[PDB]
Picture 1 (spheres, rainbow, N blue to C red):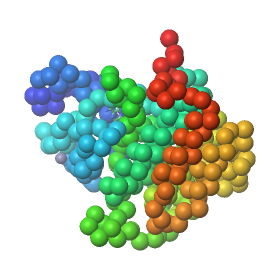
Picture 2: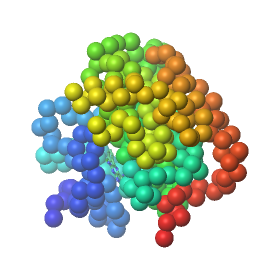
Picture 3: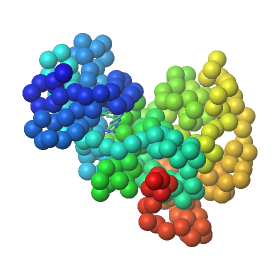
Length: 287
Ligand SMILES: Nc1nc(N)c2nc(-c3cccc(Cl)c3)c(N)nc2n1
Ligand SMILES: [Zn+2]
């Protein structure tokens, strides 16, 4: 019965982050559950405080989790955040690893907006993937949150807006399955690459699986990914998915994406399909 100082008592492991795991906590003062991350103070390169600072900078944005506390306690740096609902990977598995197009579109609208918002705060996420999007609880059950800023990087100076310099020979950060082509080529990640990754996430949700799943391991995914044309990958699915991916791959390193354009592609498709904008996801139809 490990206790994070007075305030919180730790519970089971619930998650796996880019640096360190996530535990269920109880706030003793509140009669309330929370999510807790721990870092040994002796860690060679501490990042827990650094990551909390990002969350705090972002606070108030739609779909950004709130940090309850960040501090040192005994031999650990601790981050406590508000508890959220399941990740989209978790939900994918409950929905037979296939989402309806309606669900995909409702998600793609929110997810594009979260990536826009982070970019508005001068950061890129760099690990866009299903596991890093979580649904809210209660009244926020309809809301998609983005999480985990452990691989996040500032892409421009906050005052001047000077963009980070172009570089090559970078080792890959984030999941290779959803990595952009340029990431596989060693190019420094920029705003383009968050969006491209999301496009593979979206097709992943459409397909159940990507062609580069389940095949030096890197060189293999990179090959298959570069060897599959977007036309091929998206075949049988509305052209918008391929238009999305093409647009992202066209963007130059420091280019600002047109987020509206990409949201509009999907809004218009949504309209042509006659779906209700009621935020009824596939998992809400489960019973
Ligand atoms: N159900 C739930 N709630 C959360 N709030 C949560 N949070 C994270 C996360 C990621 C990075 C940093 C921190 Cl503190 C938490 C995670 N991996 N899983 C989570 N699962
Ligand atoms: Zn701190």
